[PDB]
Amino acid sequence: TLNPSARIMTFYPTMEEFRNFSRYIAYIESQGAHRAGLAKVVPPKEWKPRASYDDIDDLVIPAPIQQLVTGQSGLFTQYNIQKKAMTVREFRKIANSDKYCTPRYSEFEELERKYWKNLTFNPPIYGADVNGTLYEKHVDEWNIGRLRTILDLVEKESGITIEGVNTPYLYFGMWKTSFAWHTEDMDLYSINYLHFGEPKSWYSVPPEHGKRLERLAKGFFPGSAQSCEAFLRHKMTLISPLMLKKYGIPFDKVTQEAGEFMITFPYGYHAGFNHGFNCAESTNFATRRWIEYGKQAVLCSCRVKISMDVFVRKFQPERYKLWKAGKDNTVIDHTLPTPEAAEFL
Ligand SMILES: O=C(O)c1ccnc(-n2nccc2-c2cccc(O)c2)c1
Ligand code: NI
Ligand SMILES: [Zn+2]
């Protein structure tokens, strides 16, 4: 529970360290960041992915979703109602209005209590999964739109576009909008940058304890678990930090403020909520460590699947026959950093 090996680390790279994305990820894994499932990276003060955000009031959010939550005793299920399209302007009006705005709070822990006490009431609207990017064309460091990781093999060799995985998504938040407990698609890494506005709070379970979270949820949602062997992948399940403490799931929390990146690691369960009107940009990425997580990922069996053949042939040609036949049973040690990190010791 308390073990700092599994606690969320924050990093403050210099501009020189920053310019190389894949290398900095390898560095933060050399320092154990991946054990927590989530890390924060504050960029160098000077760096700026856009001049300013005054000029986006006419951006269209095609499919805003109202987030209806049902439940009690810290277990909840989140349903989506697609609303018809609206602009950033229309969205900010609702968000900053008096029916939807951030309540009064002295500190994080007060706002958290109000979140878990009030998430079933007063359903907010989330401008989620908007295709696009808010970086200017000219930004070369940590550009969510083009990160140059090996994930690029899906598009380059397989010729496949997957929206929000291979491509960036924007998220327009408002108080009490939520992301439920999940790992990424195919258990990829993710990157999330908060462009502006109020903060985003995150909960994280270390990858070494993720199966504990799955067994908690199977047990609390037996119906869901019979229908689909990865029902968390549906992104409808909210579980409170008080339930996690109560059943001995270790977890950590952290708050992302405007201008910060969050990195999620393979098989890092995460959830959270936005404090008020904000905008984030995110996509998935991979390292060589990801490949084993990809091969082994348990997928939604009832409704994103990436073909691993390209990755195994390119990076594990020795193991390919064995893997195709069903014989490869490498076991993942979640503690080990990516091979790319050998240069740091
Ligand atoms: O909306 C977020 O702030 C957020 C944060 C972290 N991860 C997610 N992810 N990651 C993959 C897919 C989602 C996602 C996307 C849309 C709604 C949702 O509840 C979750 C979304
Ligand atoms: Ni995520
Ligand atoms: Zn399913």
Image: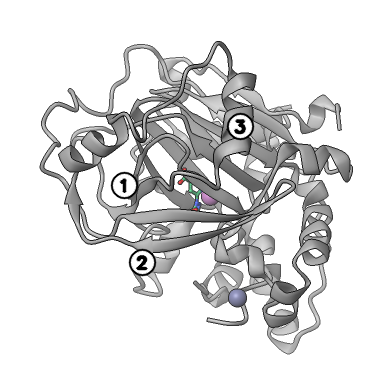
Question: Which residue shows up at 36% across the image and 66% down it?
Answer: 156
In the rendered view, does 172 fall on the left or right side of 250?
Answer: left
Q: Distance between the residues labelled 1 and 2?
A: 15 Å
The answer to whether marks 3 and 2 mark residues whose Cβ atoms lie closer than 8 Å is no
Query: Could you tell me how far apart the alpha carbons at marks 3 and 1 are, in whole angstroms?
Result: 20 Å
| Comparing labels 3 and 2, the label whose residue is closer to the camera | 3
Residue under label 2, please give it. 156
Give the spatial CA distance, label 3 vs label 2. 29 Å
Q: In which quarter of the image is residue 278?
A: top left
The C terminus: image quadrant: top right
Going 38% across and 54% down the picture, which residue do you hit?
66
Q: Name the residue under label 1.
A: 145
Q: In this view, does 44 lie to the left or right of 38?
A: left
* Amino acid carrying mark 3 in the image: Ala
Q: Nearer the viewer, residue 220 or 255?
A: 220
Identify the amino acid type marked 2: Lys
Q: Residue at x 71, y 46 (%)?
A: 74
Res. 19 in view? yes
Q: Could you tell me which secondary element the residue under label 3 belongs to?
A: strand
According to the image, label 3 marks what residue? 39
Q: State left or right for residue 342 relative to residue 59.
A: right
* 283 vs 72, nearest the viewer: 72
